[PDB]
Length: 5
Length: 263
Ligand SMILES: Nc1ncnc2c1ncn2[C@@H]1O[C@H](CSCC[C@H](N)C(=O)O)[C@@H](O)[C@H]1O
Image 1 (cartoon, each protein chain N blue to C red):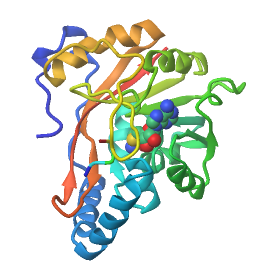
Image 2: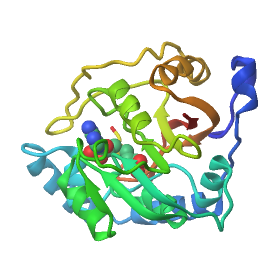
Image 3: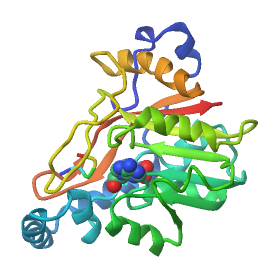
Image 4: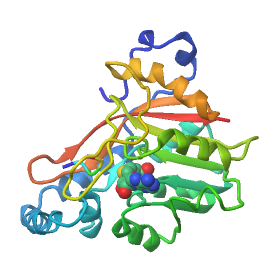
């Protein structure tokens, strides 16, 4: 997914 | 699409300090490389198996730092320079990227600095920062060092911190008062959480009072939070917070509000 989330 | 803002939903003050961005050849090459890296299904399957096994006892950021996956993009050299309102042949001494991650946005900011310092909480990404030859500080070391940094960047850390206002005051502490600036970035709508093992959230111990419903309302709410610490917005922009792709999507994007702050 997105590494921030 | 990603760079637009309705400046009429901004107060008259913030309408003047706005800085517009557009797609760059750097944004283009990042999106291209992320797409072609998102094409190799077999490698993503390897990554997926290792991820599933290791999530049982690691953080998702730590896993993506172990596998070299999920690099991100905030601005390009062009956008960063025109936001800081600096020249290409412009150089100062000290830089501090708090929560630097894998250092690729710290890499984009590096050429304009002689000393690049960093703080991180996932040792797997700390090794990647060190492999980029960065002086890794602690969570309690960047504040009490004896230096006064010229540029401090807390890009995308307030969402992922336990005491963000304390951090803002700490930044105010070790920033050069005369010509020192803070590059900050927030995912608006404000989604604040502290990570745990396996991709689990945890609420912060200090929650910021950014009350709004869209990007424009929350950026209108930010001035007060920045004012408590000691900072004022001198310029700010809207950018996409991009990340490499997996097996389901080829790229990922988030709505970022980047600010440059004055003491
Ligand atoms: N208390 C803390 N102090 C320093 N870094 C922290 C932290 N809490 C979380 N982090 C780190 O902050 C990172 C946020 S991802 C944002 C990084 C962004 N691409 C940049 O270069 O600026 C995560 O990798 C996480 O490990």
